[PDB]
Length: 190
Ligand SMILES: CCOc1ccc(Cl)c2c1[B@-]1(O[C@@H]3[C@H](O1)[C@@H](COP(=O)([O-])[O-])O[C@H]3n1cnc3c(N)ncnc31)O[C@@H]2CN
Image (tube, rainbow, N blue to C red; front, side, top):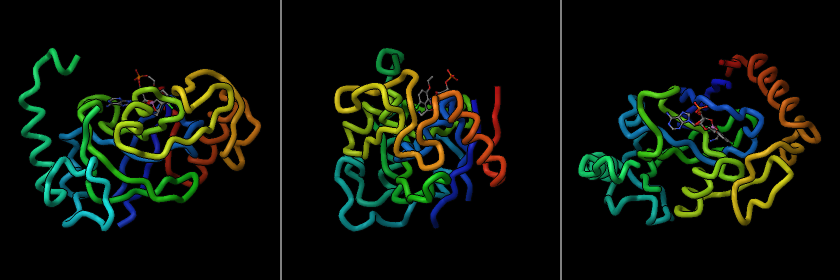
């Protein structure tokens, strides 16, 4: 595994990933609904042109987050066995320097890992499903499959990943951790 920091564009969000090699394909972040940084990161207003699917029908991000927390409390074990809300704010992907939107979603569990994930819809089917439901970008960074039909979860060759390009998955995992450590923004972890 690895832990990595994503800076708030406007605070650091630590994610745990078993696929640090896919960092150039991380197109959004997802925090557990109960994550301690959520209230900090919530924007006062929706950005202009926000996708209505992202707002939970709330007039402001704060109202939407409060409603999401209240609603998911009405779920049972049956439901818990993809929904979410945009916080109105962005983090910076440390690999490509690009802004990525921050969500909460109940598919991310508060007391596991760091309680936050980087979402890589190209290569994690859970993220693929969420991205399709919300209209988020799906980017291929591991050649081998067909991301238009499903997440590609296997081994392959790095693409669209700058200094990782051409590497195998195991080689790319080592390279990106090296880069994270040189920048002081992540670590390999068991
Ligand atoms: C299992 C396959 O995981 C994959 C597979 C492919 C890819 Cl590209 C990735 C991941 B992985 O998603 C995180 C983390 O890595 C992985 C940790 O799962 P393991 O059971 O602890 O090994 O699950 C996810 N995870 C970490 N903390 C979590 C939490 N609190 N709640 C829900 N899921 C969490 O990162 C990427 C981008 N999503």
